[PDB]
Image (tube, grey):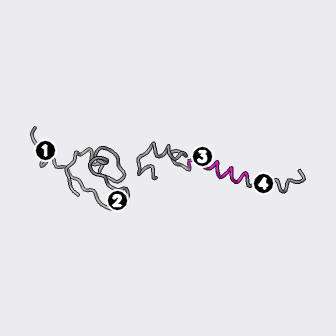
Amino acid sequence: DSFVIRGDEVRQIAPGQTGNIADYNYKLPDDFTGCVIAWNSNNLDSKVG
Amino acid sequence: SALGKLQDVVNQNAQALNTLVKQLSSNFGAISSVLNDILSRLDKVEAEV
């Protein structure tokens, strides 16, 4: 499962979390078996303005 | 006092149920002994612990 996110909100991409990303964008199950992999993408995903 | 051999059997069984009920008030090292209090203070993963 793939997307871009703000670096602060990466903590919401974990089992049993609550918050605007967890509850309104992407919710993981509590009994999740898996790996969450993130990397900074400021060189690709930002724009001047 | 003479009938006290039957009265002690009544007393031990009252004491046993009062001990069992009083042990609902104990924390056992948890944050609280009240189950709705735990579930109000903490989010799912910590409340489960």
Seen at 23% across and 58% down, the residue is A1
Q: Are marks 2 and 3 on the same chain?
A: no
Q: CA distance from mark 1 to mark 4?
A: 78 Å
Please give the residue where the numbered disc 2 appears in the rendered image: A32
Seen at 9% across and 40% down, the residue is A48
Out of B1 and A45, give the one closest to the viewer: B1
Q: CA distance from mark 2 to mark 4?
A: 52 Å
Question: Which numbered mark, 4 or 3, is in the foreground of this view?
Answer: 4
Residue type at numbered disc 2:
Phe
Please give the residue where the numbered disc 1 appears in the rendered image: A46
Residue type at numbered disc 3:
Ser
- Near mark 3 (Cα within 10 A), the count class, few <14, some 14-19 or many ≥20, is few
Contact between labelled residues 4 and 2, with CB atoms less than 8 Å apart: no
Q: How many marks?
A: 4
Magenta run includes residue B15:
yes
The extreme top residue here reads: A49
Along the horizontal axis of the image, is A33 left or right of B40? left
Chain letter of mark 3 equals B
Seen at 48% across and 45% down, the residue is B38
Residue A24 at x, y percent in the picture: 28, 46
Out of B38 and A25, give the one closest to the viewer: A25
Residue B36 at x, y percent in the picture: 50, 45
Earlier in the chain: of badge 2 and badge 1, it is 2
Residue B2 at x, y percent in the picture: 90, 53
Q: Secondary structure at mark 4?
A: helix
Please give the residue where the numbered disc 4 appears in the rendered image: B10
Per the rendering, the mark at residue A21 is none
